[PDB]
Length: 123
Image (cartoon, rainbow, N blue to C red):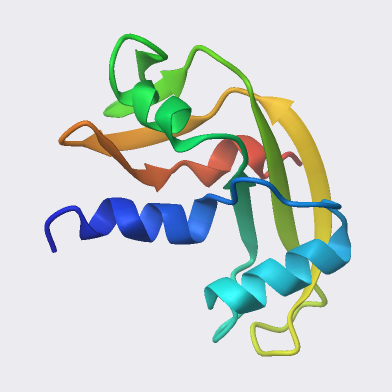
């Protein structure tokens, strides 16, 4: 799976331009992306252009972080979908939280392949 990890990243965490980042948006995009067989308990999408997210992998927009991660220097429009209900099986009900801040990703070959969801599990 060469560069198939980056594609998967985009599929689970990227949405160039959403419209309303409300609950319905979450239930819709989570379903559409297929993050609904067992319902994912929390998932965050990054908005904006891809060039910017990719740059987090170079010093252009990233800083080393924790063990083996990278934290972006710029902020991103973001939407976090939190599962609601206490059942990992559909229908999957999500609560949306729109936000604006930097993100933490893991890079491989200059490409994002993992988003650290911990900074959004804003408890």
